Image (tube, rainbow, N blue to C red; front, side, top):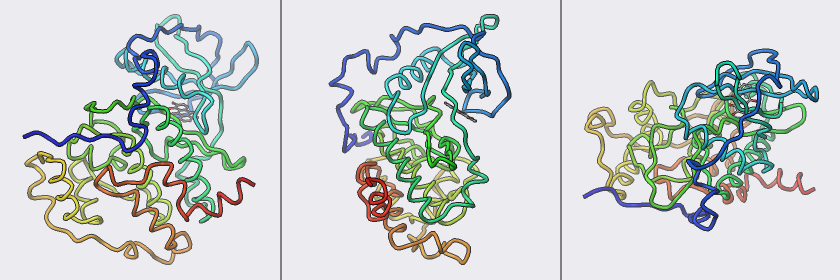
Length: 332
Ligand SMILES: O=C1c2ccc(O)c(O)c2C(=O)c2c(O)ccc(O)c21
């Protein structure tokens, strides 16, 4: 037989209750602006499939960000604009300000309001125990909002979280892999970035949901508290799952496979072996122990589960004891 089906435990049917227009992005009609409204200042970096520049809107002297898109299918560009439009103004979501083409090259680009940050490569090292709870909290607000709106991000990782540490603000960026959740849909598993891929993607289970983003969050949490970036460091997709199996063990992994009747690629037979599930204390040492607490480990353990159904939802994650003091500090 084939694989056993699966549904999200929350927000299962929110797209069904919307007008078709909200999620039927193939039919979205885009009005394209003129890129001559913007003068590029400097190259800032790259998205998953784009080049990103600092620019100035000359009509109002406003600082913006210009993301010039690499040639991708026309419906994927529609998908990202529609998702950005649907999510605009929500907590911690990057704000799309305009859409343009370079009049000469025809090439499409998205214009975001400017947000300044400190690179994660520099930042993580400086973070206090409190700071990790704080920003994790802020991330979880962006995830619960997008999940509640019918949308999985599908590329959660440190590069995609811009933190203005000076002002204690954060934005979730790069929505070019995000999709609408619909019960029963079978999604492409070639998404996310290797170290942050859920076991669902690695074993080729196509009927996944919001809970994918929560695995990615847990990978991030693990790198921050153990001071090890990235936490699961595989060389390719297969070895990514060997490295998880040596932490979480092989017993739950095979129970996982049995439950959903997943056909394992024969290539996994000899490399996976047989591994016990390890106690988190193994990763604690003198450089990181100030960030590790019984509260941190309980939370972490409830994110990193093979069985996607059994991971915390964003909203549950926000009710965890690990966040009690940030909740108290906030409101107010
Ligand atoms: O603001 C974005 C930004 C805003 C929205 C995006 O979708 C995005 O990919 C980026 C982005 O990749 C980026 C970057 O790679 C380097 C510096 C940045 O300021 C950004």
